[PDB]
Amino acid sequence: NHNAQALNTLVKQLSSKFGAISSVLNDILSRLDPPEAEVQIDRLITGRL
Amino acid sequence: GQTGNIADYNYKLPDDFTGCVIAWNSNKLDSKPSGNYNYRYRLLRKSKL
């Protein structure tokens, strides 16, 4: 159970925003220009790491 | 990170540009009553530069 739970959490936090516009990277890249998208991607990377 | 006609079709600075942009008015020298048509800018390109 513990193992499964950990994995589920590790996948569930892929859907978390971590202070960005959306959890989907492609949505952020499509909607925002590269200079503005850099900060959103940076927040997502910090959260996921 | 600026979007606009000049930025995308004439001269595009990089996202991580390191440099100084210096601008000063030239109306006293480069303006003619008849119309100085020497200076030109591009307004139709196939893709972004």
Image (cartoon, rainbow, N blue to C red):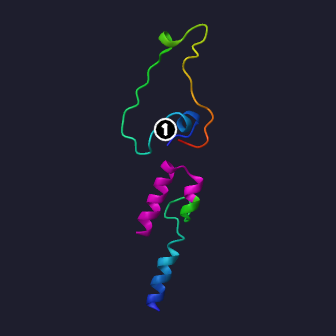
Residue A3 lies, with reference to residue B47, above or below; the image says below
Left or right: where does residue A8 sit relative to residue B33? left
Within 10 Å of disc 1 (Cα), the crowding (few <14, some 14-19, many 20+) is some
Q: Is most of the magenta stretch helix, strand or loop?
A: helix
Q: Does the segment drawn in magenta span residue A33? A: yes
Residue drawn at x 59%, y 55% is A30
Residue A10 lies, with reference to residue B28, above or below; the image says below
Left or right: where does residue B22 sit relative to residue A13? left
**Tag count:** 1
Question: Which residue type does callout 1 highlight?
Answer: Lys
**Residue reaching furthest to the top:** B33
Question: Please, what secondary structure does the residue beneath circle 1 have?
Answer: loop
Which one is in front, A47 or B6? B6
The quarter of the displayed image where residue B9 is located: top right
Q: Where is residue A41 shown, x and y percent of the image?
A: 47, 59
Q: Where is residue B22 shown, x and y percent of the image?
A: 40, 26
Quadrant of the image containing the C terminus of chain A: bottom left
**Residue reaching furthest to the bottom:** A1
Tell me the subunit letter for badge 1.
Answer: B
Q: Does the segment drawn in magenta span residue B16? A: no
Q: Which residue is mark 1?
A: B12
Residue drawn at x 44%, y 66% is A47
Q: Where is residue B18 shown, x and y percent of the image?
A: 36, 40
**Magenta span covers which residues?**
A28-49
Which one is in front, A46 or B25? B25
Which one is in front, A41 or B45? B45
Q: Where is residue A12 shown, x and y percent of the image?
A: 52, 76
The quarter of the displayed image where residue B33 is located: top right
